[PDB]
Length: 56
Length: 56
Image (cartoon, chains in turn yellow, purple):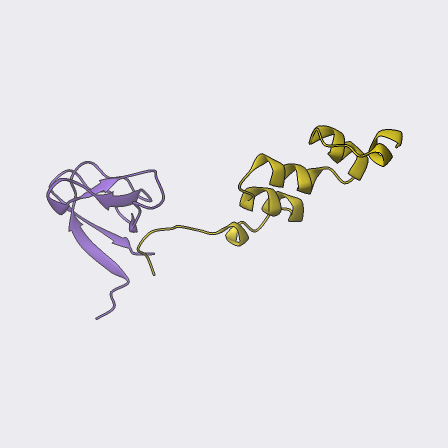
């Protein structure tokens, strides 16, 4: 049963749903997409705001 | 003949319950880093003595 333990994210039993999504993510942009739910706040943090984002 | 436990020459001093890995000349030595662990000793052994422990 043993060669090496190259476990995967879903082997970590007490990881949370957002926690596993973050562990799998490859870039900062991907992490921001997981963490920031408010679309106007996400737009500010991404430095990319529409006039609607600005008003909001 | 799937053995549940082996008798391996100790490469050092081994305490009961110590996790074991390969050492110099293929001897069994104490470890602490899961991946290198192939078995746990069930008896104390001095360097050069056989130690019998379960695989797992």
